[PDB]
Amino acid sequence: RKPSLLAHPGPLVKSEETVILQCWSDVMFEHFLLHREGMFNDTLRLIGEHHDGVSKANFSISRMTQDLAGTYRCYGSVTHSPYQVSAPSDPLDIVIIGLYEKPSLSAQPGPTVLAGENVTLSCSSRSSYDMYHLSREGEAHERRLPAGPKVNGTFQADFPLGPATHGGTYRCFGSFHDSPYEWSKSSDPLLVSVT
Image (cartoon, rainbow, N blue to C red; front, side, top):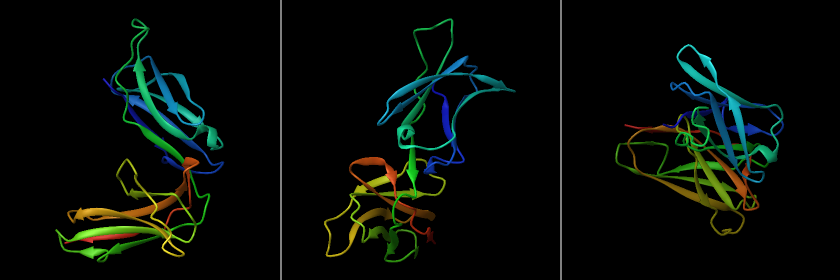
């Protein structure tokens, strides 16, 4: 069975700041394997610490650098079965943010709608970002879309939210094709409310 993987304080890290990745399972794993897919692929074996019912292991990053950015997954293991590991934790993208000008985030028809209204959030900027990333507070994986051709000055991606059900606070970021885990500064948060 797969462990959990979380970043403290969060997966979106400013350049040279710290982040700690933690693997944990209510299953008493002796060791955890933390695997990163990115510019520098690596798999680290961490010793599981037992904390009253929980087994967990940390991988601490003192200064966030692009070599540590990427998609991470954790596996739990036990020594009586050295050649087998648990199913993988859900992937967690550790990204470096705050590297470029923050984009603009707007909602159509607007940020306050009735349930069912078809809402679209648009991320835009004068910077020539190749991709935009949409983050919703409290929701795990960022959505992404390629920026639309420059419509004379502006580069933008339109994220459909579909018929409104639940509100949320959204933020967005731009990135370049050369580096999928290096993003701009966050747009100002947008609160979408649904009645």
